Amino acid sequence: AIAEQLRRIGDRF
Amino acid sequence: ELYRQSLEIISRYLREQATGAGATSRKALETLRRVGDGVQRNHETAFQGMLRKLDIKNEDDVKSLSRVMIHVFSDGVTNWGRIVTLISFGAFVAKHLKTINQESCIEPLAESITDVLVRTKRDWLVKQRGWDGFVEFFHV
């Protein structure tokens, strides 16, 4: 779940 | 070339964040302050929870962030947003480490981040024009 959140934040850009 | 430049940029941002004080590297630093402070404030609650779970409190817990990085990239997706987010979280961690007087760990933290980025993504970085591509990606 930490990975899923960092991925989501980064893929938002 | 790319490792040294990446370490200079990442460690300068981390040290500046923990202690609150060429042209490509300057604008990359300028970018990290704008975007990286933004990510940190936009995601403060989530970052707090993450730091809590990871429980990074001394220099042997520093390797946690490099494990997080490998996990993040394990779906095969690479982009500048993820890289800036990982560096932003690293800055969030270095801020905490200084408060518990673990300044011992700031640079090893920046080294671990740089290690994963350059070793596992070297050619993607080069193809993307390195820190010049970072700046252009987040430009005005």
Image (spheres, helix red, strand yellow):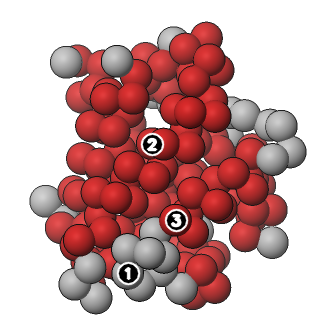
Q: Amino acid at mark 1?
A: Asn
Residues at circles 1 and 2 in contact by the CB criterion of under 8 Å: no
User: For mark 3, what is the residue?
Assistant: B63
**Can the viewer see residue B42 in this picture?**
no
Q: Earlier in the sequence, mark 1 or mark 3?
A: 1
Vertical order, B122 against B55 (above or below): above
Residue A10 position, x and y percent, is 68, 48
Q: Amino acid at mark 2?
A: Thr
Quick one: quadrant of the N terminus of chain B? top left
Q: Nearer the viewer, residue A1 or B60?
A: B60
Residues at circles 1 and 3 in contact by the CB criterion of under 8 Å: no
Horizontal relation, residue B76 to residue B124: left or right = right
Q: CA distance from mark 1 to mark 3?
A: 10 Å
Quick one: quadrant of the C terminus of chain B? top left
Horizontal relation, residue B115 to residue B122: left or right = left
Give me the chain letter of mark 1.
Answer: B
Farthest front residue in view: B60
Q: Secondary structure at mark 3?
A: helix
User: For mark 1, what is the residue?
Assistant: B58
Give me the chain letter of mark 3.
Answer: B
**Which residue is at 22% across, 72% downward?**
B103
Residue B4 position, x and y percent, is 31, 29
Vertical order, B62 against B81 (above or below): below
- Disc number at residue B83? none
Q: Nearer the viewer, residue B92 or B44?
A: B92
Q: CA distance from mark 1 to mark 2?
A: 19 Å
